Each structure stands twice: as structure tokens, then as C-alpha cells.
Image (tube, rainbow, N blue to C red):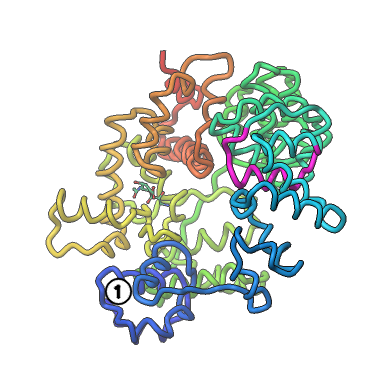
């Protein structure tokens, strides 16, 4: 327990934020303490923000240049000068709140200078503003209306849909309606997007979309364009896997099996082609200890800032300094950045705490820890998940106090490897018992067993099918969980291998198909 005066002498960081949040939820931050505190918050988003605002609410902020513009309402906007009228018409809710005659008057005012406003003003004089905006092919208006309400759904012709990808909002638009299975008329219309007009994630998601309609030839073209444009090798591998699954061109599978990225797609391709398992680095530092305190979360924030802001000369001196058994997690963290992510590091720190579990469970624990924290004992996420296993504080207190009844339990115990591993094994036992597959366990570990059960109970998710289970893995409705599951599954395959408990990744996929 650090007092608010001690914390103010620490660097702004997620760890300092976390401890400020702890004072706040304990009601130990007075109104006078809170005055200068917004400057002490590394990330003023989310629960620390709403908690601090129960003490000192911010009424801010309106730009003093446009202050007079917000003293008007729908009833008096025709009294406002021209600049205030245009300012207030940035909000589609404001536009919707006007009456028809005023929208018509304002539409005439702006048809010259701001035809975008005119189109929206007149769209809202109809029973379907989206249909009006689609007929004008007003791309900016289309996305403002989509952001205003997802409920609009409408068929879009070839000319219109091929103009949508040029807008910054298109990637999130397409991802959202495809992985949530919403706006079917939008989704069906995006079959007509020319692959030349999209790239990267947008092209990949349009390939997934094409597969849901069994347009395999259009899907192949989208995935090929994604493969040729993706920046990261991992994503490119994902896209090449789909090219192979659709057309079985064995040069695609060959490229996938030779990839430098270690992921489930390249692992699967290696297995399908009798290609040997990729080389895993071996890290056995001869030195045993140094000065660094692996239980000080402020020291980790400190050194993590340095490492992420180093050239090479600094990386090399850091690598040498943390080349000890004690700081093995930081050593492998540095080495991963030093080698520009081209080498594969799969350490097993604090191994005594798990060496007595069966090797399959050890692999799942290690796979989770690697993805969650890179084995940093004092890791703190932006929602204040804690320690190597990144336990959310609520779940950690339920287990620590109500289940395991640990004497004098504080949530900061999660920063201890033996607690993190013990709690992670305990929690994984709960999830494995309900879900079986390590993939599903991964989804529920990251996103809770709530949405996993909801997703598994749908009849279009991880059932049998031409492209299953791979298609379902692309349609997991939360992007974070979708990615997390693929990454943890790869880690799990690797660790089962290093533990001499190898498993064929093809067996993992067979078990995902519920019959
Ligand atoms: C073991 C555990 O705590 N799992 C939790 C997970 C985790 O904390 C996070 O993935 C760390 N990055 O977060 C959430 C969440 O919806 O916030 C749900 C899970 O119950």
C-alpha cells in the first residue's frame, strides 16, 4: 500500500494508474487530493476516469471559439449565424431533431458551400435517410449515417460499394457487420467489391464474407489480394492458408510451410507436408541473479519504457545486463525485440511451480502466460489485469478469498509466479472441464466463459461444414478473442512439443467440429 503522496513521486505509467485506482475504489482519495490528479494519470480512460469524475466531475470541454454555437437548440438554430449553423449540423442527432421546414431552409442555405450538409438535411426529411444518401452516392454521408445508427440496411450497387473502401471508416464497418452477422443487405452487396479496390484486413474480411455466401472464387481473389498486401507475415500466412483451402494449389501450401512466422497456419502447413518443426531458441543464462527486483511493478514500467525506446547499442547493453536466471522473462523480452521478432522464444520460467502438473496442462498454462504477459511477473494491462497470468482483479479476489481462502490475500499476490500459476491452473481446470478444447478454453480465458458458451450454442459456429473449423475461427464476434485464440493455440502446440508431449495440430482441429 502506497500513499497518494508517494505515488505522485513516481513516473506516470499503468502501474501508477493502477495504484491510484486502488486508492479511489477504497475511497482514500479526498476531493483536495483529486485536484492536481488528472495530470498524474498515464491513461485517463475507462474506470479510473469515471471513478475520479465521481469526485471532481469535468463539465469540459467546448472550444471557446464555438461557445456561442451551443447556446442554440433545434427551436432557435435559424437565429444562429452561418458558422454556428454549420457547426451544429455536424451531429446527425441534431439534424434528426429539427423539423422538416427548417431542414429544407437549411438545405438551401448550404447547397452551394456544404452539399454534404444539404444531402443529410434532405435525407432526414424522408422516411429512410440511408436510402436517400445511397442514391446520391454520398460516401461521407453514408458513414455518418452508419455511425449514427447500425439499423439502416439496404442493397448497394456495384458503383457504390466500390467507392466505400476509399473511406477510413470502411475497414471497421466491414469487419463489424461481417463478424457480427448483421446488415445482410450490406454484406451481400460487398460481394461486388472489386479486389483491386481493397487491401490488407479489408480484403481479408471480404474474403471471409465471400465464403459465407459460398462464392469461393470471389473469396480466393480477396484472400490473394490480402496475401499480397498484408504487412505482417502472420496475417499473410492466414490469407495464404485460405487460398490453399479454397483451390488446393500446392505452391501456396509450400509457401505457407516455409514461412518465417510461427502461427497455427504455418504449423499446420508444416505438418501437412512432412516439414520439420521450426527451430525454437534455447535460453540458458549462466549468471543467476542481478540487482533488478522482479516484484517491483514500477521498475518494470521503467525498464519497459527503456527497452521499447532503444536503438541497438542500448538493446545490447540491456540484453547483457538482464542475462540472468532471475530476469529470464526480461531477457527473452529484450531478445525478441533485439532480433526484430525473427527468432522464436518459448521460455518456461518459475518452472518448479508447474513441473508436477501433467504435461498437457503445463503447456496450456505456459501458452496462456506467454500470450498474456510474456511471463513478466508485474505485468499490468490497461484494464488492470495483473501478473503473469493477467487475472482481472475481481476474479482473482473471488478465487483468493472465497474459494482458496488464502490467509491475508491481496490481489497484488497475482504478481507472484507461484500464485499466478496456481490460480491459472485452478481457473483453467474450471474452463477445461466445461469446454475441453484448448482453443475454446483460450477464448473463455480471454473473454469469459459467458460469450464462449453463447457462441458455441449458435448452430453456425464450430459445427460441421466444408471449411470448418477454420471459418468459425474467423467469425468469433470479438476481434481481441478471435486473435487471442489463434495465438494461444500456436503457443500450446509449441509447448506440448518442447515438453515431449507432442500433438498433431490436425487433431486439435478435428476436435473443434461438434457433430
Ligand atoms: C483469467 C482472467 O482473469 N480472465 C479474464 C480476462 C483476462 O483478465 C484478460 O484476457 C487479460 N488480458 O479478462 C476478461 C474481461 O472480460 O475483461 C474476462 C476473463 O474472465
Q: Which residue is drawn at 64% across and 75% down?
A: 68
Question: Quadrant where the N terminus lies?
Answer: bottom left
Could you tell me residue 428's position as x and y percent? 30, 40
Is disc 1 surrounded by few (<14), some (14 to 19) or many (20+) residues within 10 Å? some
- Identity of the residue furthest to the right in this view: 112
Compared with residue 140, is residue 223 higher up or lower down, i.e. above or below?
A: above
* Disc 1: which residue: 23
Identify the main secondary structure in magenta. Answer: helix
Where residue 141 sits in the image (x, y, percent)? Answer: 73, 46
Which residue is more in the foreground, 228 or 250?
A: 228
Residue 139 in the magenta stretch? The answer is yes
Is the CB–ligand 1 distance for label 1 below 8 Å? no
Look at the picture and state if 40 lies above or below 449: below
> Judging from the image, what secondary structure is the residue with disc 1 in?
helix
Q: Quadrant of residue 253?
A: top right
Could you say which is closer to the camera, residue 73 or residue 301?
Answer: 73
Residue drawn 49% across and 20% down? 460
Q: Which of 404 and 112 is in front in this view?
A: 112
Magenta stretch in the rendered image? 136-152
Q: Where is residue 156 in the image (x, y as percent from the top left)?
A: 74, 29
Q: Position of residue 381 (x, y in %)?
A: 43, 60
- Count of numbered marks: 1
Q: Does the magenta segment cover residue 190?
A: no
- Image quarter for residue 213? top right
- Asked whether, in this view, residue 294 is left or right of residue 412, the answer is right
Q: Can residue 19 be seen in this view?
A: no
Looking at the image, which residue is at 36% across and 30% down? 453
Amino acid at each position: 500500500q502506497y500513499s497518494i503522496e508517494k505515488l505522485k513521486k513516481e513516473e506516470n505509467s499503468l502501474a501508477k494508474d493502477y495504484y491510484i485506482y486502488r486508492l479511489l475504489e477504497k475511497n482514500k482519495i479526498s476531493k483536495k487530493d483529486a485536484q492536481d490528479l488528472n495530470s498524474h494519470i498515464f491513461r485517463y480512460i475507462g474506470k479510473i476516469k469515471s471513478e475520479l469524475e465521481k469526485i471532481i466531475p469535468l463539465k469540459p470541454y467546448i472550444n471557446p471559439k464555438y461557445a456561442k454555437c451551443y447556446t442554440y437548440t433545434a427551436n432557435t438554430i435559424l437565429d444562429a449565424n452561418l458558422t454556428c449553423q454549420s457547426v451544429r449540423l455536424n451531429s446527425l442527432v441534431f439534424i434528426a431533431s429539427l423539423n422538416s421546414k427548417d431542414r429544407t431552409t437549411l438545405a438551401q442555405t448550404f447547397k452551394n458551400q456544404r452539399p454534404d450538409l444539404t444531402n443529410l438535411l434532405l435525407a432526414f426529411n424522408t422516411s429512410d435517410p440511408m436510402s436517400y444518401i445511397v442514391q446520391k452516392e454520398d460516401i461521407n454521408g453514408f458513414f455518418k449515417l452508419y455511425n449514427y445508427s447500425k439499423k439502416y440496411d439496404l442493397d448497394l450497387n456495384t458503383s457504390l460499394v466500390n467507392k466505400l473502401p476509399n473511406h477510413i471508416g470502411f475497414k471497421d464497418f466491414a469487419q463489424n457487420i461481417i463478424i457480427k452477422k448483421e446488415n445482410p443487405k450490406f454484406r451481400h452487396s460487398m460481394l461486388e467489391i472489386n479486389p483491386e479496390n481493397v487491401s490488407e484486413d479489408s480484403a481479408f474480411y471480404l474474403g471471409v464474407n465471400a465464403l459465407t455466401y459460398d462464392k469461393t472464387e470471389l473469396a480466393y481473389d480477396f484472400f490473394k489480394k490480402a496475401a499480397q498486401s498484408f504487412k505482417s507475415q502472420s496475417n499473410k500466412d492466414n490469407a495464404i492458408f485460405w487460398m490453399w483451402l479454397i483451390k488446393n494449389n500446392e505452391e501456396d501450401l509450400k509457401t505457407l510451410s516455409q514461412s518465417s512466422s510461427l502461427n497455427i497456419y504455418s504449423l499446420y502447413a508444416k505438418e501437412l507436408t512432412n516439414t520439420p518443426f521450426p527451430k525454437i531458441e534455447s535460453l540458458n543464462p549462466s549468471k543467476k541473479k542481478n540487482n533488478f527486483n522482479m516484484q517491483d511493478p514500477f521498475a518494470w514500467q521503467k525498464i519497459n519504457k527503456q527497452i521499447r525506446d532503444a536503438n541497438a547499442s542500448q538493446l545490447d547493453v540491456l540484453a547483457k545486463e538482464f542475462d540472468t536466471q532471475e530476469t529470464l522473462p526480461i531477457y527473452a523480452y529484450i531478445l525478441e525485440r533485439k532480433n526484430n521478432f525473427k527468432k522464436h522464444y518459448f521460455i518456461m520460467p518459475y518452472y518448479d511451480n508447474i513441473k508436477d502438473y501433467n504435461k498437457t496442462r503445463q503447456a496450456l498454462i505456459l501458452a496462456i502466460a506467454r500470450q498474456e504477459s510474456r511471463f513478466i511477473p508485474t505485468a499490468i494491462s490497461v484494464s488492470y489485469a495483473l501478473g503473469m497470468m493477467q487475472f482481472m482483479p475481481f476474479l482473482a479476489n473471488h478465487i483468493g478469498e472465497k474459494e482458496l481462502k488464502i490467509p491475508n490475500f491481496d490481489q497484488d499476490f497475482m504478481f507472484k509466479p507461484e500464485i499466478a500459476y496456481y490460480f491459472g491452473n485452478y481457473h483453467l481446470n474450471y474452463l477445461e472441464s466445461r469446454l475441453k478444447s484448448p482453443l475454446f478454453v483460450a477464448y473463455a480465458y480471454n473473454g469469459g466463459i459467458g460469450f464462449t458458451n453463447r457462441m458455441l450454442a449458435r448452430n453456425d459456429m464450430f459445427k460441421t461444414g466444408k471449411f470448418e473449423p477454420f471459418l468459425s475461427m474467423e467469425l468469433v464476434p470479438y476481434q481481441e478473442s478471435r486473435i487471442y485464440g489463434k495465438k494461444v493455440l500456436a503457443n500450446y502446440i509449441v509447448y506440448r512439443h518442447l515438453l515431449n508431449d507432442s500433438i498433431k495440430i490436425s487433431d486439435i482441429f478435428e476436435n473443434l467440429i461438434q457433430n
